[PDB]
Length: 157
Ligand SMILES: NC(=O)c1ccc[n+]([C@@H]2O[C@H](COP(=O)([O-])OP(=O)(O)OC[C@H]3O[C@@H](n4cnc5c(N)ncnc54)[C@H](OP(=O)(O)O)[C@@H]3O)[C@@H](O)[C@H]2O)c1
Image 1: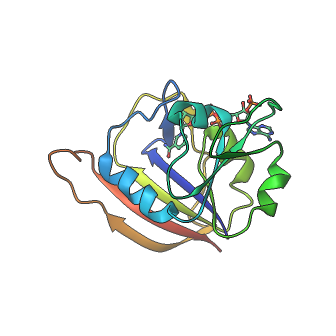
Image 2: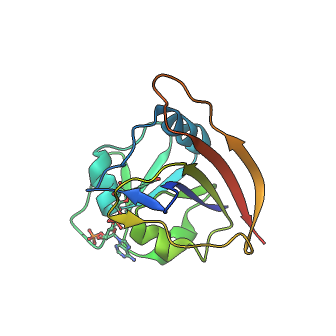
């Protein structure tokens, strides 16, 4: 199973200066819940910004750099390599990977961040006429989680 994993704002901003534009602990908990025990594929810039593999899942980095060899990370050098990855595979950014994979994934787990942030990277436009809402759940807010957000699971029609 091949799934997109992403948080984007009302204008589909996903990043600014190689980091998330928002601070939202609950969404990171959500994404770790979805992906534990599975596989995260990420482009090189996204990986470098995280800086270290996420524990308790297979971390795969897509890069053209043949000198890339990081402890606890598997490297791939083509999109085609993604299809050889066994199990539930999550496409986890950044913009380049989303653009390359959005026409290929089975479904998408999207957190809509219900705000407008300054961004330099975007999730590609998509339409609900291609995607059925399997679920839509409003995130609960508190002191440390102050931006309204909605967890979507969309499945390709
Ligand atoms: N909001 C979210 O849920 C979320 C999640 C993840 C990331 N992000 C954001 O996304 C932004 C980064 O996106 P980005 O597009 O700048 O970078 P990126 O997708 O993270 O990485 C781009 C790099 O990935 C490698 N790559 C991509 N396609 C390739 C291919 N077909 N063959 C070989 N290598 C390939 C290349 O690495 P090389 O140059 O080394 O060859 C390319 O330069 C950051 O701001 C980050 O915060 C947001």
